[PDB]
Image 1 (spheres, rainbow over the protein chains, first blue to last red):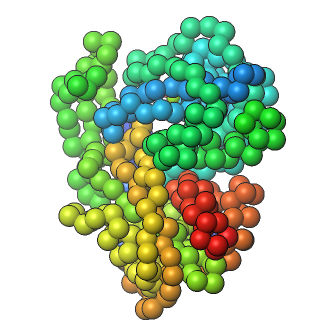
Image 2 (spheres, rainbow over the protein chains, first blue to last red):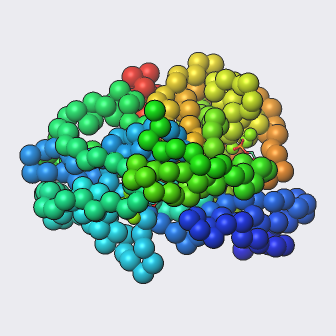
Length: 182
Length: 182
Ligand SMILES: Nc1ncnc2c1ncn2[C@@H]1O[C@H](COP(=O)(O)O)[C@@H](O)[C@H]1O
Ligand SMILES: Nc1ncnc2c1ncn2[C@@H]1O[C@H](COP(=O)(O)O)[C@@H](O)[C@H]1O
Ligand SMILES: [Mg+2]
Ligand SMILES: [Mg+2]
Ligand SMILES: [Mg+2]
Ligand SMILES: [Mg+2]
Ligand SMILES: [Mg+2]
Ligand SMILES: [Mg+2]
């Protein structure tokens, strides 16, 4: 029941990111070219909290912005992998950590006007570093540990620029207070 | 002081969205191809609240997701336009509304791994419909009015799928409580 009809779907790029340019007939009966990153595609985000009430985060270079941003560990869900498995895998790769319970938080689309990607946030409890990180070529980041009170102060001060990290923190807050970690 | 050095920047598309494919030399001294939507580019998001404690939102088709999403009015900042002016302009175009004070909320990057875009959220007070909407070809949406209590119930229930709308609501909440609108 799509309101727009496909006329022609052209692949503009296949790797490292698939991008398409689609000519469609809109609700006005006119034609329009829409450019986007097609689905199905997803990524998992995980706020790793330790038993000491601290969070394991990453300070990561994000080339398009030219900045190093404070973010929760996160990454693309591989083919046939569940969001929870991707969350645990990226946590291990980026911070060298493992966790016990992973509480699922509301999923969201970071930029639905351009990409079909769905981001799956999680709150990981009893997070602990157990091995050295294993980063891919392309990943420039350092892991760090911050008291939850400081992380939420930064959030309140509007200093968390990565939207997904900020949203994950907002969704995690009530759970953290309930669990007595915040 | 960029950690990555440009080898060659190729434009893959100029319109309707500019996209580039850049070959860079990374921190490992190796080469990598990075694909992204270059800056400077921005959009403004505005939560329009009425004097009756309701919010003016839009139910908008987002083609990449194939869904109609509940969002706050928002749009691209045009060349040489300020974020506040874009917020007021898109509010007028999409909902046919005007507002009095616009309180700036923390700006954020929706997906820094892929786009340089910065989103500028605002809380608009005394919002009121004054004219019919003026939508562009490409915009398929309907405006609606919901009590703030219902909007925040939806947020708490994890039903707000658009990340920017969800984050704008979280940042706006303390202000709304302070002002006595929530
Ligand atoms: N837009 C992009 N262009 C090229 N590589 C990307 C892009 N987005 C993410 N990557 C790469 O994918 C890798 C791992 O990402 P992640 O699964 O998100 O933790 C990194 O090394 C990135 O460089
Ligand atoms: N990725 C895209 N490809 C083609 N058109 C787009 C894309 N993203 C946004 N637009 C168009 O830009 C218009 C107004 O957007 P906005 O300023 O965001 O409210 C809409 O009519 C959209 O169809
Ligand atoms: Mg990652
Ligand atoms: Mg990965
Ligand atoms: Mg990774
Ligand atoms: Mg818009
Ligand atoms: Mg616009
Ligand atoms: Mg618009």
